[PDB]
Image (tube, rainbow, N blue to C red; front, top):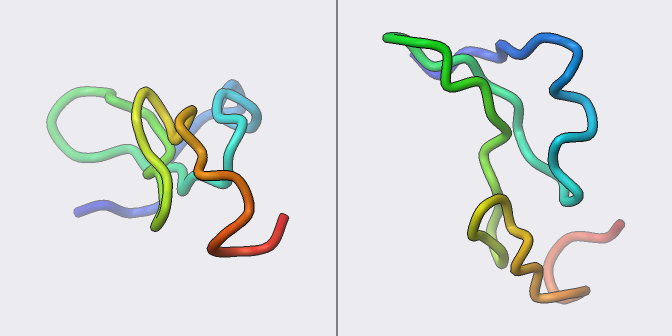
Length: 53
């Protein structure tokens, strides 16, 4: 269901990593946040602690 789906405008909408998806139903195009940070879009990044750049 959560297959990789996201037009071009979804290549910088998120400042953090983010995993672009389309999600069934309606649009909802977005980038799944990650482990360590979240919010509108991990805007609340716990800085460097998890991944690496």
